[PDB]
Image 1: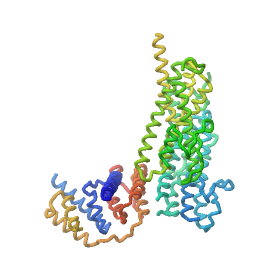
Image 2: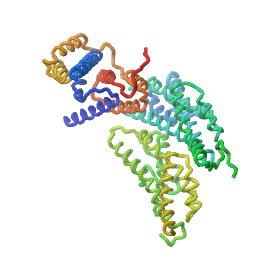
Image 3: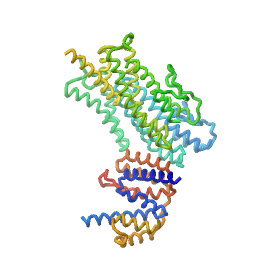
Image 4: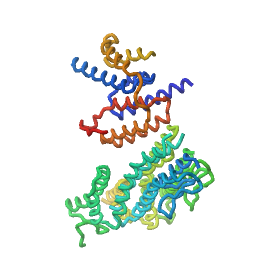
Length: 67
Length: 196
Length: 180
Length: 108
């Protein structure tokens, strides 16, 4: 049963990876589950998306400043 | 019967294949539901609106099969049939997705909503179909350049793909005629007629 | 109910599908779980299935030298070329089988959408082969019936004809090279 | 496992730095999150998928849209969650279009 859960999680992760690669989102595998599952606790999808966008902008700024 | 039963019959109908209590009527050249699923005319009309998909798909199958087996009607005609085959393959892929959804929510409205665009593509195809009969050879290429005189960027792009594919045979003939002066025209369809 | 329908189309008739020798790839129509028109699409595929059965019979009969039928390296080469073309068909069938086995819900409609390409290239080759058998051409006669059809219009069929004709003209080239 | 622990770890990953190194960024994100914890629009994946396909067509990616629709069918067949709409909205907001030059017409 738990092996079934693991297999289903892997399958969902692969489906999500394909969806992300098709969307060309640029989101990393680190947001494999942590990104989606944390919002799965009932986070405001608009607020979470805005927070992700702010994190992306800050990360881009940090990369540019490091460069 | 159940609205889901009608949904399954429609899941068959979209391929042009009539359902259990839904049958392809000859009276209307379209799908007339088998009245033994006594229900509201609202759902009846929803299927009646969807019947155009079946009528056009069956017409496409019959018409493309006609020129597919005619080898001497023109390789251009066979090429038009092949392009229609690719388009029908896309439609069939959509229908397969639909049947998979029929396996295991959605809605007839959602079905119609998701089916509206294929209806538009099929309408464009059927207009090109009945609007192209008889024109072969340079007449065929004439119709190809003629039907491209409309807008609808979606339909415009579909017709553009069809015509650019149609150019390849004529382009090859010209390339033979322009590169070698070679005119092996069997059906005598090329612009440069042969006098052997 | 997918795997056996594929086996029946694989050149090995099943049980709900009866490969009548003269009735083609007929189908015992007594099973549940589909619409007869779904069975009708399956019958459109069974057209190709019966064509494959007959093609296999012909290829094995033309792959055996003393018979009065058409003979020569040409017949064996035609059988070999048809088999090599069926290799893309066999490979596609195997890929589709793997995909259907991999998917919990892989619709036979999806199987049809995958097999549409082979069904598109199939009938023209079937007509050409039936014509060649009716002509009973031998020598470079079939080599010229081929050259007549090598101006084909079906892109997959045109390319397959180009490959088979390349193989044939290679054989002719070998014969002429011996003569040279 | 806590939503705050997840936020701290995610901020550390997004910055590629420590949680204390992202504490100000973490503080801003925490303010943004506590500003709104639940979505103000319902979950109806038909419209979400419609928007996704519309964006793909605006990206001239009709084949990719078909691939995405097939992936959606497979994923809904492998349905394991109940609020997928939010994940889909996240994926759409995370989506980028390197396949097309930046120029768009405003929708309604």
